[PDB]
Image (cartoon, rainbow, N blue to C red):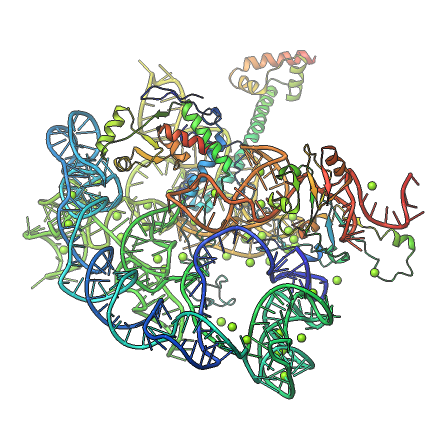
Amino acid sequence: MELVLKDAQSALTVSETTFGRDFNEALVHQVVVAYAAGARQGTRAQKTRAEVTGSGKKPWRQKGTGRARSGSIKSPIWRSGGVTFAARPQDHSQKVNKKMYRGALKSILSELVRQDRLIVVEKFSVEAPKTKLLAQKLKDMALEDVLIITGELDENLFLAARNLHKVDVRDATGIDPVSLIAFDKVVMTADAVKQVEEMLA
Amino acid sequence: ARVKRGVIARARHKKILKQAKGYYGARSRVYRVAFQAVIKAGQYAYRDRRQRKRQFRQLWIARINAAARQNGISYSKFINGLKKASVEIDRKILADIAVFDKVAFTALVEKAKAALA
Amino acid sequence: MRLNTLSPAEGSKKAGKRLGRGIGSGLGKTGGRGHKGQKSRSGGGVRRGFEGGQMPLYRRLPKFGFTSRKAAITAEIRLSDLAKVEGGVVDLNTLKAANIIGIQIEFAKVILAGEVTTPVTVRGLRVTKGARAAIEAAGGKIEE
Amino acid sequence: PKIKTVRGAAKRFKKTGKGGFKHKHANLRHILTKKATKRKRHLRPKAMVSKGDLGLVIACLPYA
RNA sequence: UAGCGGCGAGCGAACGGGGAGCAGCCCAGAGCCUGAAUCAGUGUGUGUGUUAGUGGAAGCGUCUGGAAAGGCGCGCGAUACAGGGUGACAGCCCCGUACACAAAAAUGCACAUGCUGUGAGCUCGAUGAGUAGGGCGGGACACGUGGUAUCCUGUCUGAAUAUGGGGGGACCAUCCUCCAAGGCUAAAUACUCCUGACUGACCGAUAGUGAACCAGUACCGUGAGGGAAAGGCGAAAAGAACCCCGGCGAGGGGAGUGAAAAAGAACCUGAAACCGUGUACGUACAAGCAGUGGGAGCACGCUUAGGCGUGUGACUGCGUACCUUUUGUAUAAUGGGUCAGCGACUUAUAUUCUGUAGCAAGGUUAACCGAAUAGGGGAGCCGAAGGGAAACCGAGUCUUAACU
Ligand SMILES: [Mg+2]
Ligand SMILES: [Mg+2]
Ligand SMILES: [Mg+2]
Ligand SMILES: [Mg+2]
Ligand SMILES: [Mg+2]
Ligand SMILES: [Mg+2]
Ligand SMILES: [Mg+2]
Ligand SMILES: [Mg+2]
Ligand SMILES: [Mg+2]
Ligand SMILES: [Mg+2]
Ligand SMILES: [Mg+2]
Ligand SMILES: [Mg+2]
Ligand SMILES: [Mg+2]
Ligand SMILES: [Mg+2]
Ligand SMILES: [Mg+2]
Ligand SMILES: [Mg+2]
Ligand SMILES: [Mg+2]
Ligand SMILES: [Mg+2]
Ligand SMILES: [Mg+2]
Ligand SMILES: [Mg+2]
Ligand SMILES: [Mg+2]
Ligand SMILES: [Mg+2]
Ligand SMILES: [Mg+2]
Ligand SMILES: [Mg+2]
Ligand SMILES: [Mg+2]
Ligand SMILES: [Mg+2]
Ligand SMILES: [Mg+2]
Ligand SMILES: [Mg+2]
Ligand SMILES: [Mg+2]
Ligand SMILES: [Mg+2]
Ligand SMILES: [Mg+2]
Ligand SMILES: [Mg+2]
Ligand SMILES: [Mg+2]
Ligand SMILES: [Mg+2]
Ligand SMILES: [Mg+2]
Ligand SMILES: [Mg+2]
Ligand SMILES: [Mg+2]
Ligand SMILES: [Mg+2]
Ligand SMILES: [Mg+2]
Ligand SMILES: [Mg+2]
Ligand SMILES: [Mg+2]
Ligand SMILES: [Mg+2]
Ligand SMILES: [Mg+2]
Ligand SMILES: [Mg+2]
Ligand SMILES: [Mg+2]
């Protein structure tokens, strides 16, 4: 599998099972759903009839009066009563198998290649930590909505990309499928390709 | 989430209350009565699509029997004449001719009498 | 390929029953429960093996046997597991290092199941007759 | 939580190779001088659980 | 799971393995060297916080509009496009944010060190008696007295003591291991009255705390105690000068403010039940779930008169509500005065089946680490072999002396 580079106009040999795999949509949808469920915080609760502030005394007697039977003012059919199935703080995280997560990444990186949404350069640096310099460089690259993966830790690049919402900058380890889909273009350092190929076999 | 269902239950009640226009009293004002009256109106409408086809055939037959007895033959003779003369005119058209064109009904009667004789 | 073009596989997601939401849903007023039983009650139902008041099967029938503690520390070994060790020698400590039998195991037999294609010295373990023939045919040396 | 095994059925039934259950016969514990030896001889060996009562056993023995 | 158990309902380990975290010491006593380690307290010094704070970038024109932050142009900042406010939606109006700093004084935490007290180390010893154990009665151990080890003790007793004793699940023997009847000890662990920061596929005023509002209030009760309802004018009060009717009223009509007063304080939007005024049609010889099918007439619109619509509905065929429960209800069996709002098959963990997806005789990790939805981690679990009560045998095995 060969990836031509943008700036120096060279080639780069990669694995076809990694960057030319057929798109398994149901796998990718399963992984993207589990990622968005892992982001889910799940902090809520309501009060049951056990947890409503009140007293456990019958508001009226069982019979003799003309009214309907009632045992508690905390009843979930009363105003300001409990919730019938009041919620608890629950964890919405799903398990994703490791081979299914890597199958999804190899699927969507093959699709970004087939859709020309993947740009490969040797290096992508900004000299001083300025968003004006980064926006100038991305305008010269004709890029607006982009993910920038770098096989190193560039602090000036992190600072120059922190204020731009169209732009996100990741390490090659910290890549995720929903970002790789949510961004229009993805720029990879050739080192980041080598690291992604090592992680993804 | 707490889905608040006021909009849906309002439009669902107004769909029934619009169908219940013209009804007397709470049948046009009250959802519990109107919905109970719309279902019965659909039952009657399903029934009376069948009863329309009965009642018009009965009306047509009574008009043919009258015009045939004006020309001096009964209905059952006249239909047996038109069967033996093979005349396949349905009795909507026979009632229409029996009203507007009594001459053509007389010619049909004479064909039926000649088919019986 | 965007987030509004993904879709799951066919038959993967099924909707799920919602009891007590109208005639047309099928699961109407009763919700699959019938009328006026114990089963229709909230929390209702009988426990396992309850046959009415009839004497259940697990008490009509007698107890039998006992439990051998030595069977929990015995194990059986395929011939296909003999290649997964290193050194070409097979002991208990080698199989436990290969995570085959487990730590608390003190006895093991080798059984004719699978097949081996390499000479393996077996030491301190019982061997069946067919595994003895297959090991000795592949070049093995069963000893103690 | 885990399901708890009905320990009497675990002392009364054993799962076989294809998933069936073996069990001991009844009527062979006392009152044995009036029973024919043919009957006892056909009661010593273990029998399989029938198709009708195999559901209550599986409900009692969830962990095989 | 092993077991316990009217062997019922149910209760339910341990050994061992993977991890977080790790820390050891002293008196039952004399000497020898004497203040030597460590700890406590109290000072001092430095650093780091906390308790007030400071600076903090960069926009104009035009159109609509009551009002520009909106639209259309043209620029600029960004380690600051977190957030909020400003007359509609503001990176560049304001407060802030990123970042950079700041404490007279009090105080926390680290070190360092001063002082007080504390003893350090070596040698030789000593080695926790009404105790262990036992009998009786109870209790705890997963173990309900059972064949029941072990632990506790109310009662009665009662050892040996390093050549000795305890345990190894009745018990004895051998062997292994440990040394009771004196104590101390950080971390990993549990929780949140309270404080600060931030977050939410949490609520949005019958919800969410009982309480968005002077709510544990009003009110009730002798009392303990119970326990509500009730949010929104407008951008800004500019909250209606003045005139008129009226009781020096209430209330209203003008005028005025305002973008708007059918935003006027009983104030955003203002649905329904319910109650009215007006118009059209029908109705005082006509019997019943009140409709439906047909259908005259009248009124009103459109229109090339073409005739369609709309409203009403004389007369006429048929037609005894809904729900529930029932063999079966117009039933004179239940329930509902009506409207609006709320109101009932959920959640967690195990297990099985189906579907679907991944790998495939293999599949998969949990804890945890990790800045971290990755990767590591294969403790383990399920499966690829079963039979037998079991030892055991093994594609066979059990039964039996042996199986046609
Ligand atoms: Mg009481
Ligand atoms: Mg509530
Ligand atoms: Mg309340
Ligand atoms: Mg993981
Ligand atoms: Mg809600
Ligand atoms: Mg009305
Ligand atoms: Mg019922
Ligand atoms: Mg019944
Ligand atoms: Mg039933
Ligand atoms: Mg219940
Ligand atoms: Mg009985
Ligand atoms: Mg016996
Ligand atoms: Mg300031
Ligand atoms: Mg500023
Ligand atoms: Mg506005
Ligand atoms: Mg001692
Ligand atoms: Mg004792
Ligand atoms: Mg004893
Ligand atoms: Mg005792
Ligand atoms: Mg004693
Ligand atoms: Mg003892
Ligand atoms: Mg023993
Ligand atoms: Mg001690
Ligand atoms: Mg409201
Ligand atoms: Mg409230
Ligand atoms: Mg006034
Ligand atoms: Mg009002
Ligand atoms: Mg407003
Ligand atoms: Mg209003
Ligand atoms: Mg109204
Ligand atoms: Mg009249
Ligand atoms: Mg009249
Ligand atoms: Mg009912
Ligand atoms: Mg009855
Ligand atoms: Mg029935
Ligand atoms: Mg009856
Ligand atoms: Mg009837
Ligand atoms: Mg009546
Ligand atoms: Mg009734
Ligand atoms: Mg009754
Ligand atoms: Mg009633
Ligand atoms: Mg309602
Ligand atoms: Mg399930
Ligand atoms: Mg599946
Ligand atoms: Mg056989």
Q: Is residue C128 above or below residue A108?
A: below
Q: Is residue A175 above or below residue A53?
A: above
Q: Quadrant of residue E378?
A: top right
Report the image quarter containing ligand 11: bottom right
Residue E92 or residue A21, whichever sits in front:
A21
Residue A140 or residue E392, whichever sits in front:
E392
Percent of width and height locating residue A36: 42, 40
Percent of width and height locating residue D13: 73, 52
Residue B4 in sight in this render? no
Q: Is residue C80 above or below residue C52?
A: above
Residue drawn at x 37%, y 32% is A182
| Left or right: A86 in relation to E33 | right
Percent of width and height locating residue E103: 15, 59
Percent of width and height locating residue A128: 22, 34
Residue C16 in sight in this render? yes
Residue drawn at x 91%, y 60% is D34
| Left or right: B40 in relation to C133 | left
Residue A147 or residue E317, whichever sits in front:
A147
Which part of the image, by quadrant, shows the N terminus of chain D? bottom right
Q: What is the total number of numbered labels drawn onto the structure image?
A: 0
Residue A90 or residue B113, whichever sits in front:
A90
